[PDB]
């Protein structure tokens, strides 16, 4: 009786998998970069520590993404000034220890993301959290900032968060070679794997679907390969569709689509050459 009746209610939620009502509350209008790029209600990140008596207080334009054909991710839009505190609430509650920013703050005179970290050696509050930038390391393609975050009501409860910003991947194109992105993801994965208890990796660009979707799909495919071997079914189209069921529009452009193929092809060839050496 019960499970059959329950299944009859599971039906409605299946059909509702494409709704994006929360992002359309009038209270949330200033929290979106684009009125038409909204998180699916079913997978949206719901902010805690907020007053449920205030409509929209739980909102952020971001969704959980998991590899439903295999670690997990959050795909987020890039901060507006009005949403920087919301971003830090999200990172704290999810226990995220790695942030992956795939955009510059401004590209070609267009705002993409406001900075939500302090300069090195600076400490400041973002709502009820204190964030300190403890140091930076520059490579040719990306910058790593080590942030220390703690609740203002619990000052000694410190978490280190590693913030990786890719600097050479414009919203209007893709990198000329995939090597930079592949080594960037290798460092990110080494960091994440070193922390079994860490929450989802937070990945963002400007709208949170283009470069964000592209880098997440590359990472999931690399994971699949590293786990199953070079024998595995690599189905890029299927992987993208799976990720699109969780946040609308992930992997936006034809250049991004081709870049996934180019990145994975190089990853496979590099892997094969190393294995050839070991045998």
Image (cartoon, helix red, strand yellow):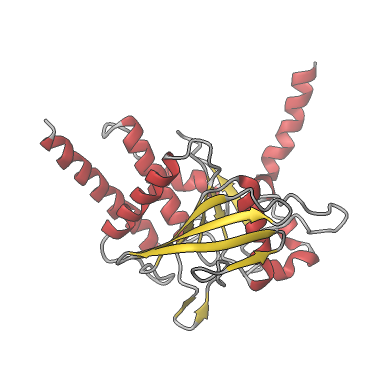
Q: Residue 200 location, x and y as percent?
A: 54, 45
- How many marks on residues? 0
**Residue farthest along the front direction in this orientation:** 156
Whether residue 39 is visible, yes or no, is no
Q: Residue 85 location, x and y as percent?
A: 67, 63
Look at the picture and state if 28 lies above or below 2. below
Going by the image, does 2 lie left or right of 190? right
**Which quadrant, please, contains the N terminus?**
top right
Whether residue 36 is visible, yes or no, is yes
Look at the picture and state if 58 lies above or below 220. below
**Which quadrant, please, contains the C terminus?**
top left
Going by the image, does 158 lie left or right of 210? right
Q: Residue 8 location, x and y as percent?
A: 75, 28
**Residue farthest along the right direction in this orientation:** 53
Residue at horizontal 34%, vertical 39%? 234
Going by the image, does 195 lie left or right of 256? right
Q: Of 112 and 163, which appears nearest the observer?
A: 163
Residue at horizontal 74%, vertical 53%? 153
Q: Residue 4 location, x and y as percent?
A: 75, 20
Q: Please tell me in which quadrant of the rendered image residue 89 appears.
A: bottom right
Residue at horizontal 37%, vertical 43%? 221
**Residue farthest along the top direction in this orientation:** 1
Q: Of 16 and 229, which appears nearest the observer?
A: 229
Q: Please tell me in which quadrant of the rendered image residue 60 appears.
A: bottom right
Look at the picture and state if 142 lies above or below 66. below
């Amino acid at each position: 009786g019960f499970w059959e009746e329950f299944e009859s209610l599971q039906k409605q939620e299946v059909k509702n998998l494409h709704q994006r009502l929360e992002g359309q509350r009038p209270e949330n209008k200033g929290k979106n970069r684009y009125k038409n790029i909204l998180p699916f209600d079913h997978s949206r990140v719901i902010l805690q520590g907020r007053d449920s008596n205030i409509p929209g207080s739980d909102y952020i334009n971001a969704n959980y993404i998991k590899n439903q054909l295999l670690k997990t991710y959050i795909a987020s839009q890039g901060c507006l000034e009005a949403t920087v505190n919301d971003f830090w609430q999200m990172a704290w509650q999810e226990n995220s220890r790695v942030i992956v920013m795939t955009t510059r703050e401004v590209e070609k005179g267009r705002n993409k993301c406001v900075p939500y970290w302090p300069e090195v050696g600076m400490q400041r509050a973002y709502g009820p959290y204190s964030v300190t930038n403890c140091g930076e390391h520059d490579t040719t393609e990306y910058k790593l900032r080590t942030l220390q975050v703690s609740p203002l009501d619990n000052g000694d409860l410190i978490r280190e968060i590693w913030h990786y910003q890719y600097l050479s991947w414009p919203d209007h194109g893709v990198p000329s070679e995939p090597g930079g992105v592949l080594s960037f993801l290798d460092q990110i994965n080494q960091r994440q794997e070193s922390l079994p208890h860490a929450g989802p990796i937070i990945v963002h660009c400007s709208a949170g679907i283009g470069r964000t979707g592209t880098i997440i799909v590359i990472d999931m495919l690399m994971e699949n390969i590293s786990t199953k071997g070079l024998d595995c079914d690599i189905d890029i189209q299927k992987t993208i569709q799976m990720v699109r069921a969780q946040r609308s529009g992930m992997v936006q452009t034809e250049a991004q689509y081709k870049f996934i193929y180019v990145a994975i092809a190089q990853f496979i060839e590099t892997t094969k050459k190393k294995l050839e050496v070991l045998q």
